Image (cartoon, rainbow, N blue to C red):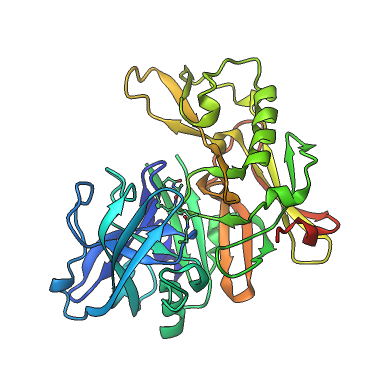
Amino acid sequence: SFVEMVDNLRGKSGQGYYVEMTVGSPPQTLNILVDTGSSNFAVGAAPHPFLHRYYQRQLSSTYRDLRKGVYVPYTQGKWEGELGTDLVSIPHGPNVTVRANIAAITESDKFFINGSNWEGILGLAYAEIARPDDSLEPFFDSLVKQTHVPNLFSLQLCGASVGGSMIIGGIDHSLYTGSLWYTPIRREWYYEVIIVRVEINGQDLKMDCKEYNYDKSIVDSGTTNLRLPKKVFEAAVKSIKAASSTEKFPDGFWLGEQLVCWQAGTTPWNIFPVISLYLMGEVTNQSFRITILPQQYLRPVEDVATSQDDCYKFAISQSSTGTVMGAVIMEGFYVVFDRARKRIGFAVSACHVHDEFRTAAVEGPFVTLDMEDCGYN
Ligand SMILES: CCCCNC(=O)[C@H](C)C[C@H](O)[C@@H]1C[C@H](C)CCCCCCCC(=O)N[C@@H](C)C(=O)N1
C-alpha cells in the first residue's frame, strides 16, 4: 500500500520538504517540514507574518495540555512554545491516527520561511536529542508504539518547484534502481554515520578520516547544503576551485554569499568535479561510496532580474558541528532510515538529476581498513 505515499512531499528549492498532516479533532490541516536532523514535532500555534495558518488548540476537543515549556535551537533558527498532546494523522501516509507530543510554537526567530508553505516541523530522529529532554517521545516512536507501522521510513527527495516521497513503514522498490547499500547508524541520537574516505574527481583527499567526522556526521533532510568541518571544507573548496580555475567567480561565491551565472544552457558542468563519500559498510573492512554530481552542489537560483542566464549558488558550506549530509546529498538517492536494523541505506534514485557524460552512483563493495578509527570520540 505504499503507492499512496509516493509523491506525498512538496516544497520550494532551498526551503525544505514538507508532508501534509492533520492535528486535532476536528482535523486541522498543516504542512509539516520533514526533518531527520531533529526529534521534536512542533507547529506554529500563534499568528506570524509568514504563516498562512496555524494550530488552534482551543478548537481541538482532543488537545491535552502538558503544562511544560519547550525551546529548540537549530543550526539556523529557533523557536519556543508550549508542550501538549493531540491526535495526529498523515493523509497520504498509513491509515492510522496516533496521539503524539506536539510543541505549540508561540515565539520563533529565523525559523519560519516566507513563502515556504509549511507551518510546522516533524523531527524524525531519536529521543536522545529531543527537547527539553529525552523523555519527550518523538512522533515516529509514538507511531511505531501505537500502531502496526514497521520501524522504518524512507525518503526520496527530488530536486529541480520540488517534490518527493516519504514512504512511512517500508521501502518502495519502484522508486530506486540498482542495489541498496547500508551504513550503520553509529548511535541513535542524530542519524549519525561514519565517512571513511573522500575523493574528488577520483583523487583521495588523503586526510585523517576522523576529520571527516570531526564532532559527528549526520544525515539531515532539513539542511539544504552539504556542510563540512572547517579543515575538510577548505580542502574540498581548494580542490573544486582548482578544477574549475578556467572560470572566474566572485569568491563570495565560494562562501555562498554571491551567485554565479552563465548564458542559458552553457553552464560548464564538465569543469566541476564529482565528490565521492565513502561510508562504513555492514561487514568487516567493507565500505561503499556515493557519488555526487556538480548539479547537486550547485543549487539553481532564479535570477530575479534578467532571467536570461542560469545562476547558481555554491551549496557546500563550512560547519563547526560536524558533517551534515543535507538535501544536496540526499536528492541524488533513495534513502532508507532502517531504524529497526540500525542502518541507513542508499540507492540511486529514480528521480536522479544526471548530466550527459557522468552519473551519480552508489557503488560497492570497497575494502577499507580500520574504519572504526574514523569515528570521532
Ligand atoms: C535540538 C537538537 C537538534 C538540532 N538539529 C539541527 O539543528 C539540524 C542539524 C538542522 C535542522 O535540520 C534545521 C531545520 C530548520 C530549522 C528548518 C528547515 C528549513 C528549510 C531549509 C533551511 C535552510 C537550511 O539548510 N537550514 C539548516 C541550516 C538548519 O538549521 N536546518
Residue 212 lies left or right of residue 37; in this view the side is right
* 160, above or below 43, in the image: above
Q: Can residue 181 be seen at all in this image of the molecule?
A: yes
Residue 212 lies left or right of residue 328; in this view the side is right
What residue appears at the point 68 percent right and 28 percent down from the top-left corner? 238
Examine the rendering and report whether any part of residue 97 can be seen: no
Give the side of residue 86 with respect to residue 360, left or right: left
Viewer-proximal residue among 173 and 46:
46
Residue 347, picture quadrant: bottom right
Picture residue at 59% right of the left edge, 21% below the top? 268
- Of residue 65 and residue 245, the one placed in the foreground of this image is 65
Estimate the x, y position of residue 287 in percent, counting from the top left. 77, 57
For the residue pair 204 and 97, the one nearer the viewer reads as 204
Q: Position of residue 235 (x, y in %)?
A: 70, 34
Where residue 231 sits: x, y (%)?
68, 40
- Residue 154 higher or lower than 315, as above or below: below
Is 280 rendered above or below residue 75? below
Residue situated in front as seen by the camera: 34 or 160 = 34
Instruction: Count the marks.
Output: 0
Image coordinates for residue 377, horizontal then vertical, percent: 70, 61
